[PDB]
Image 1 (cartoon, rainbow, N blue to C red):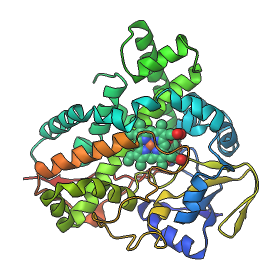
Image 2: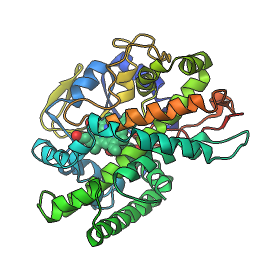
Image 3: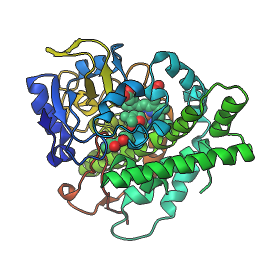
Length: 399
Ligand code: HEM
Ligand SMILES: CC1=CC[C@H]2O[C@]1(C)O[C@H]([C@H](C)/C=C(C)/C=C/C(O)=C1/C(=O)C=NC1=O)[C@H]2C
C-alpha cells in the first residue's frame, strides 16, 4: 500500500500520471496524520473511462453503513468521524438508491436549473458588494476576501440564515489536527441543532424550513437525516465553489492572454468555467465507495468489501479523453468533465455553482480587469485535504 506524502497534496496530477501509466487501480494510504481517514488502505482509481464507469457502477456503494467498516479502523465511534460522523453524514450522498431517492426528492425541485436562474439578481448583488467591501492594498488575498464569502452568502440566502462558517469547513476539510476537526464537528451539530429549533419556534419560508415541515408535518424525514441534510447543503456547497473561484483565478492569472480574452469576449465565460472545473477540480476525489461484490477495474481485481477512492482530477486530465490535459484552454470543447460526478449522485448544486462562477468571474473581469498575482505562482501552496483541492491564500493586486 503506497503511502501518500505531502508532495501528493501539492501536485497530485504528477502522481496520477505516474500511476495511470502503470494501471488504473492502486492501493494507497493517506498520511497517518490526516485527521479521519489517515492510514486507511484504499484503492485509488486513475483514468477517465475507469473513473466515469466506477462513479455509476451499481456495485460501488456510498452507504454510510458500508463505509463504517473503513472508518471504524481509526475511530469505532460513529459520531467521532468528523464530517463523516453519523449525526452529520446520514444524507443522500451517503445512501444507496431506495433512500437516496427519497432524500433527494425533498430538495431537488429547489436546486433545479430553472429554479436557480431566479436567483441571478441576488447573486449579482452579493458579488458586487463583496468586491466593493474589501480594502485597497497591494495584496488583497482574494480567496478570503471574495472566494470564501460568496458561496456561503448565496447558500445562506437559500437556507434562510442571516449574517464562523469559513473556519468550520476549514477544520472539517483541511484540519491541522484530529482535535481541530473533532472540535469543529461537535460545534456543527450544536449549531445545526440550534438552527433547526429557530425554524420550529419561528417558521419561515426557505429550503431548511420546508425541510423541517417535511419532518414534522409529513414524517418524510428522520431527525438524523434532517440534520445531515442541512450539513450537506451547507458544507457541501461551500468548500466546492470557493476553490472553483480560487483555482480558476490562479490559472487565469498564469495565462493572462486567456484571462483578457475573457474580458474581451464574455460569451466564453460559461465554457471557461467548465475548463476550470476540468483542469483544477475543487474535489480531487469523490466520496469513498465500498465494493458490494468482486469487480475488476482496469486489469486488477477489487475484492468484495474493499474501499475505493475515485480520482476525479485524474479522469479530468486523462490524455485518452482530453488533448493537452495539463494546459488551460478556455475555448476547449465543453462537456465530459466529471468534476460534478456521474450517475445518481451527480451534484445537485451544479446549476447553482455554474451560475455562481459565471457571475463572480464576469464581475471580476468588469471590476479590476488588470488585476495580477502578487507573488510568484510557485510559492503558492495547497491545503491538506483528502478530497478538497484549494489554496491557502490567493494574493492579488488590483489597481
Ligand atoms: C464547483 C462546485 C461543486 C463541485 C465540483 C461539486 C462536486 C460534487 C461531486 C463530485 C459530487 C458526487 C460525489 C460522488 O459521487 O462521490 C457531488 C455531490 C453532491 N453535491 Fe456537489 N459540488 C459542487 C457544488 C455543490 C453545491 C453548491 C451544492 C449545494 C448547495 C452541492 C451539493 C451536493 C449534493 C447534495 C450532492 C449529493 C447528490 C446526490 O447524492 O444525489 N454541491 N458534488
Ligand atoms: C466528496 C463529497 C462530495 C459532495 C459533498 O460531500 C463530500 C464528502 O465532500 C464535499 C465537502 C466539501 C466535504 C469534504 C471534502 C469533507 C472532507 C473530509 O471529511 C476530510 C477529512 O476528514 C480529511 N481530509 C478530508 O478531505 C461536499 C461537496
